[PDB]
Length: 296
Length: 292
Ligand SMILES: Nc1ncnc2c1ncn2[C@@H]1O[C@H](COP(=O)(O)OP(=O)(O)NP(=O)(O)O)[C@@H](O)[C@H]1O
Ligand SMILES: Nc1ncnc2c1ncn2[C@@H]1O[C@H](COP(=O)(O)OP(=O)(O)NP(=O)(O)O)[C@@H](O)[C@H]1O
Ligand SMILES: [Mg+2]
Ligand SMILES: [Mg+2]
Image 1 (cartoon, rainbow over the protein chains, first blue to last red):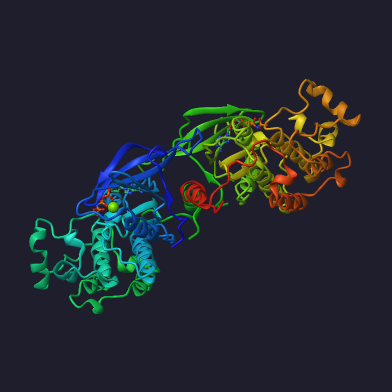
Image 2: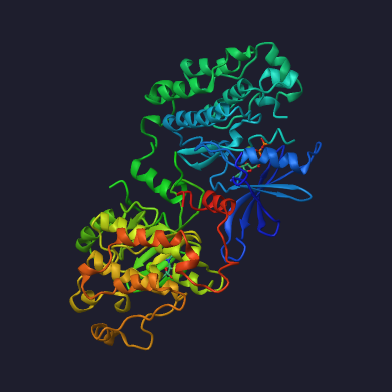
């Protein structure tokens, strides 16, 4: 792993200036990195991990980080820099749009089927890249897709679970036997797609994680999203098959959700979809040049 | 046409006043995507002379061209807003322009850095020559820094819509060709090698065209060997067809950047900053995702 792809930061190089949110693994501040000997202050995203439980040695952390920093894909967020102190602080590119989950919740009325189906494509491509790299995310969820632009999404918090439980997003084998494979990540992908098709609903609402394994071991799955058709749900329902090797491979999902994007009026049904905002070329280039710029 | 976004004056909102010049004024702007909760830092250019609907037609037409300059080393016109007066939207560069940068880093700036900016500025200018475009307003002030290791040329085609940088023929006959930009390039390079000095300082603009014909040229920058100043001087030939072409200055500078100590003599060059691989990937990943 290119040991130059991860830059070691001294705590004096950057500043916390805001709290964007917290999760099971740490707190994420919006940050500013002042290049040594420069008057500019560049927007970053510091995530401070919480040690528990229980802690890795400084060297082993580096090794895992050198791997998270070696992630090169248009749809997978890469670890830019790290900071070892009394705590460990990860540094990534600041995403102003926030996570995808929050995005749809904000826009439950404005999304077109073209958008949704495309995000499933981008997430799948991203997960596929990770799969091809023999890397297991472990923690895939719609909260963990950041929106770079409304038409470009990426995946964060990769391999954090390896350093340091999202029960309602885990496949059965992960819950019961701590098994984590590219196929368990597929199940999580299914839940994520569910989250998207329901404009930010909560998986198993009211049902305590305590016994999610129970309902699952009894064949209980999530409601067929209101806007989905059978073609689509057949796929989701396939991602949640107790037999792991029965679930779709990511490369196949790319093709599946791609084929569906060819005519999104067919696989998805939405209020103003007949006339809802499709990404215009002249609009997309503006977004890309000003905010994106990365090869994809 | 997809390159130029006609912005509604609502979408964007000026904020800080970054500066003013010959062609207009610059503000730190904010593009607020119509349906989004995001505020995104841009760079706004309010042309200093107002404009009417007919001049607008001619303006957009150039604006499409400016929107099409797709080069890592030349700034692209992202969006435009026709109103009482025309407004242009480009990327905002926190590092500011290359001129103010050299002056506030005289002692920090080493061989490798200077000789590289030159190469880049040549690449950008060569791109404009390859596309038969005439910059007209080249100067260290027009060359923006994206990262201390990646510079870009701005205010292209703004002239079509400065004496001390202009070529002789530009001053005496308002002629602007690629070789006349090669002249402005020479002065630009000079600006840098002198860590920001003013060209022909103490000599009134109206009397600049004069001294040129008597054979007066900017002095050899204190840090320049003859391999370099020979090139700067060749850019200032009276015969336009005699000065270097941009495709050549790229080569000749690339030659020197592969052995910086020799062609540029700077005190404390031995300790001077080397752009480490990691520190670079950090800048690129964070700021310039255009593979610098
Ligand atoms: N690069 C980023 N840019 C902008 N916001 C970010 C970025 N990374 C994380 N966030 C925000 O950080 C907030 C919460 O931090 P986080 O640690 O990701 O919790 P989480 O991912 O929702 N829960 P978890 O599954 O345990 O990681 C999320 O809502 C994200 O929107
Ligand atoms: N994209 C940008 N990002 C940051 N600053 C910018 C950007 N574009 C222009 N500026 C600033 O705008 C300020 C004023 O420049 P301007 O009004 O274009 O005239 P100028 O730089 O003197 N060139 P000129 O046209 O010959 O007057 C400069 O100091 C730049 O630093
Ligand atoms: Mg997250
Ligand atoms: Mg300028």
